[PDB]
Image (cartoon, rainbow over all chains, first blue to last red; front, top):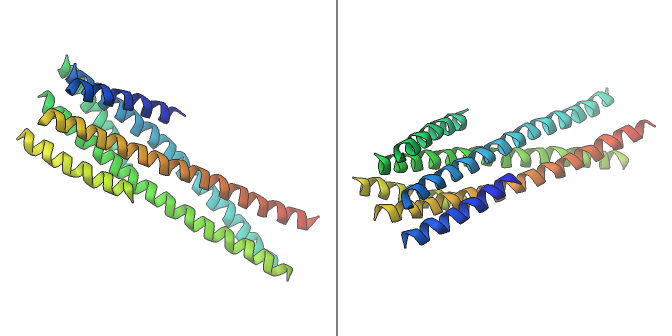
Length: 72
Length: 72
Length: 72
């Protein structure tokens, strides 16, 4: 799963920015790229679920119609 | 799709913060608002899919029950 | 809903970073942790919907097969 890789990568960069808080600006900027990539990967997965739900809707509808048509 | 607009808007702001790294703090702060907006828009879409899945669950359940009831 | 709590928490931290823009670096770093947590919580919910969709797929498939088998 890429998203968990981008999340682990962001968790590392977070610890480094916090430790460095205790190089920083560049690390904050990189971390913003990590988060943006995660959001983008999540958006891709979300789009897939939306299409999957539409597919299931069509399949259920076909079954409901079949059962209506069998009653005649 | 708003989310792809907020993602494009974040991708631009990322390039600018990276180029400016090579105005910065304000750009990092704005980029944080872009990412927050994207997460919020994704949350809205995610909530819709959760409700869509519940609707499909109810529709399948009604069909399963109909088929059980037809067996009598 | 945790995600709306993490989103409210991020919205507060955003206003503070913007007001402070008008303490900042630490607030930007903390806000990055807020956003990362939101993305992670969203990922958890997204994974649940993926599994829910698979469950519905199996349920619809069982009904489609039952109806095929009844035709004999």
